[PDB]
Amino acid sequence: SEKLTFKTDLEKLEREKAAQIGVAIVDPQGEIVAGHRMAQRFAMCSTFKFPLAALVFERIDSGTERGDRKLSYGPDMIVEWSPATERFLASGHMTVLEAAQAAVQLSDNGATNLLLREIGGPAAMTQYFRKIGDSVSRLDRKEPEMGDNTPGDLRDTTTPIAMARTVAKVLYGGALTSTSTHTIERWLIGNQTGDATLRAGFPKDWVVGEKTGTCANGARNDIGFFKAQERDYAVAVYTTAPKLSAVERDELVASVGQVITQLILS
Image (cartoon, rainbow, N blue to C red; front, side, top):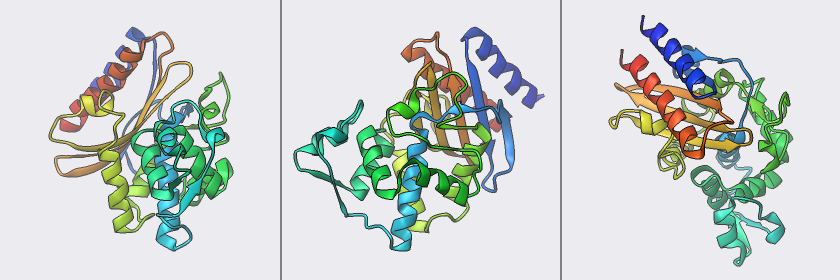
């Protein structure tokens, strides 16, 4: 069967590429379409920045945050991979929207940390997960150390199913206004970091938006949505491949995308 080909192909990739592959695909109402290691814990890496943006938009939506509010910072705010933050340093600030846009589309760590500072840190980000029905996802640390991905550590982890359901909740389950849901979706579509990952393995006809992650011990992740045959899906892929090169990890997630494609199109 179609479902058996999905399973077998993912395992074939796990053995050949020395990898753990976590996959969850849900429909708009959170119901399971397909999975693999779906309740296994993986490090979030940068994938959480998409939910971070949801939290921010919910505060804008409610009137408890302002999109053009200036977030001030000095050089101490700069950490590894902070390309937007470095550029705006001289000027002395980024706005709420600037920083969230940097976080989502460039995976900018400094901009993520700037927002976390403003919204109440890892604990607030975690309670946002809980408030929207995710009892699994947890942010414990700031970037970049939240991506240490230490053996056995439960900090800064999710599961594929918990994150796919969170994605469905943010985009299709009314957690945000229509205008805020639309902005986040465009940002996810215009993401600058995911060209060689999941969307590389989806057909060119699919509308896909996603948020990547890369962190220690060969973590390569991608979460988001696709519209296929005019149906909407939420997908979360988490993988660990410590033996693989940079490029091969990308190709691994994109290969998972092709396995997904065949299951969906069948």
